[PDB]
Image (cartoon, rainbow over all chains, first blue to last red; front, side, top):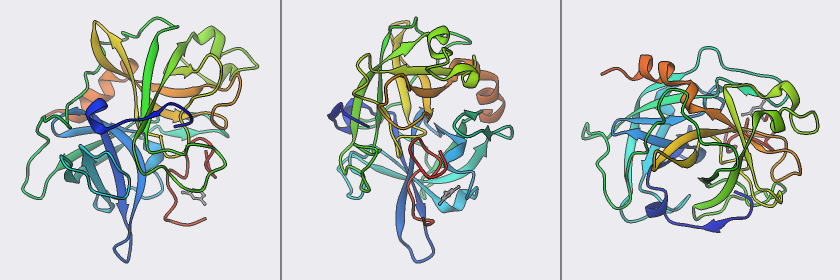
Length: 247
Length: 16
Ligand SMILES: *Cc1cc(C*)cc(C*)c1
């Protein structure tokens, strides 16, 4: 996250920190995700496409730091890794950039709500906030696009939803963005998501409910003028989410 | 680059 503020997991308790085990036993951060039910985390396929094996991955909930344990965290294995079979990218755009991870602790349990862990509501079919709405993003992504290290404490910021018309202006992204995506950014272009924030939530009030409106997906650079974040538009993926999370 | 890279296909990343 460029700009914004250091926060703690209590303030974004649906946030999932996803890591990969390496040959050697070294563990590195992959991407963010969001807890949408006790057993289910949603993320972005591009995060996993290179190494699509569920056994590689660890999911933490209730965790506020990147490479240190925090009180209230819980650790999970990935029981099912579901990538979108129509995932595709051009030079910049990612289509169907959506993944599901079924989580299970070694003791065979799903998540339990606590002061540090809560699910986030999915929107109803095609139900999105009006453009101009202020939403939140969060993650362990770069604080500056030129940095080589990642912040060790979770960050969040506020960005505003941009109309399709405006985002489909040529000096924005043109026809790179579809009805299956949402653009969001800072009016003054000083705060944004960045590398490392992929798969994490775009969270908006809607129905007076904190709602997973988007998943961090793509953009050109980070915090560049007329170059918003592009998010997978959750309200348009309910059937995919339904046909892949049946109990 | 390496297999230890964070979010290699993310925005601003090598393959974003
Ligand atoms: C160096 C690198 C790393 C990944 C994960 C992907 C690409 C295309 C290049």
